[PDB]
Length: 284
Ligand SMILES: COC(=O)c1ccc(S(N)(=O)=O)cc1
Image (tube, rainbow, N blue to C red; front, side):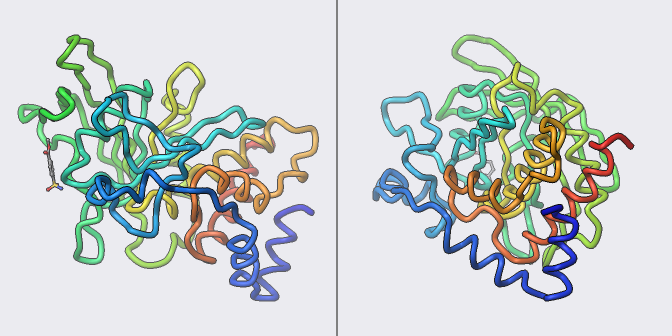
């Protein structure tokens, strides 16, 4: 069923809360035993948001390999994403170790460091060229190279150095700065513009490791970003673009990380972004 018609049918019937609860009921449940070990309590921002054991990213160290991060592998779309929490004071070194070990080109940040008057994630990147950051626990150095500030997002060029081998890589930081403190954006125009800028960078492409995507918990806004990208790619690839079922793509993604899309408003916004974005994909 053409999702644009399914959309008007749910809107006119005001049944978004009912569709959303149906997804919550059918979603996969897999063990998260490593996340719940007592040694890992200060590595988790939220007690009710954990990576599944089968899809968790492992740090390459014998001490403690744990980080709150999941690999979302979309077989038909041929895209992979790492979804993670906003880093905490005691996990900023682990975060950059993961970026290094997984060979990521891009980091996508969908939150502000402070929202609703509380800290939603650590200041994990340098704000001035001449004041670089050293992570002594993982032996990495991070320098700000350049910053391009626009009305709805900021793009930064960063240099990550492995202090053990003196190799360096360029990382791109894509920072969506205008998601509102409550609810979802009124139009998806600026969110789709942002997604097309990440794609244009090469950060989502198979020659690199998976893109790292985060918000505060790494399930809500993060979920919206990867769901919209995957649905638009499948509409490009298939003979029948109307066959793309957003609820079925979301359930496939929930096999890899719990809770993706946190509200009925985020589900509705995801439909709107795919419907408005398709009017480019189908030749405009
Ligand atoms: C190496 O860098 C750090 O050790 C570090 C720790 C915490 C914060 S934070 N959460 O206060 O912003 C920022 C940076």
